[PDB]
Image 1 (cartoon, rainbow, N blue to C red):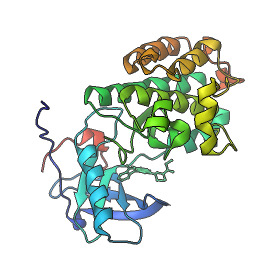
Image 2 (image 1 turned 180 degrees about the vertical axis):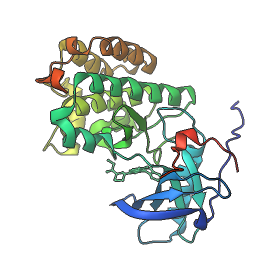
Image 3 (image 1 turned 90 degrees about the vertical axis):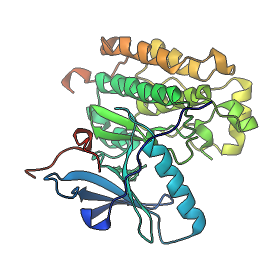
Length: 291
Ligand SMILES: */C=C/C(=O)N1CCC[C@@H](n2nc(-c3cn(C)c4ccccc34)c3c(N)ncnc32)C1
């Protein structure tokens, strides 16, 4: 059947890392920016640390550990992996710090300076991350611009395997109707995610109640063509929102298409002004040292 999962789960003693600031608090919990110093090594690694807000329930610890399980089992340049856990009364997850936050906020905040080259590269990178998950027989279930993190403006990675094996406006039709989720189901979400980026962060089907969404899609309605998108790009989004799940593109195909478009980006996205667009600190991606 499946091959054994020999990923290592690293345990971090609370004294090897320090919380420095809060980055955000929500339903998810509290996320801090911090610094990790592996014991006896002259390295400081920028990290983010996640604590579950204001509780110590047995159900809450179960889901945190499920998340850690999935994050420990991946290794790809466009996916977020776990650095370790800290076994504190409140169990903490430690991962690499992604300084620019999520891609959704980044596109919103930084829109007047985002060119076609960045947009299409993000699309490739996400498709690469997703393709890697598919290789791992892993269905995401919550792909969205809010779940892509930004290491640098040139380098993004997929995250939030909380649901990874509701966010209704990102879901394939078959998922809404029948709670079915597949890799092809993730493509639909990929399509919505691309639309988000191309609209610089608009909310899809804005001011429409989620109950209505199933009905709209059944008729044949889809998200509108964004103003910067040539028909070439929008057609790709539309193919991801095809009713027959097998008619949708494969992640591997999307890597290819978007990648071709990234070679001549101004031919596929039309954006006004597009032309005019600590001594021992080591990034987690360069720190491959065991135990
Ligand atoms: C758009 C997402 C957003 O608004 N966030 C709120 C601000 C903090 C953001 N954030 N989350 C993580 C993150 C995600 N996951 C799965 C983990 C797991 C362990 C520790 C952090 C963390 C962030 C990271 N790594 N860096 C910077 N911001 C992060 C989410």
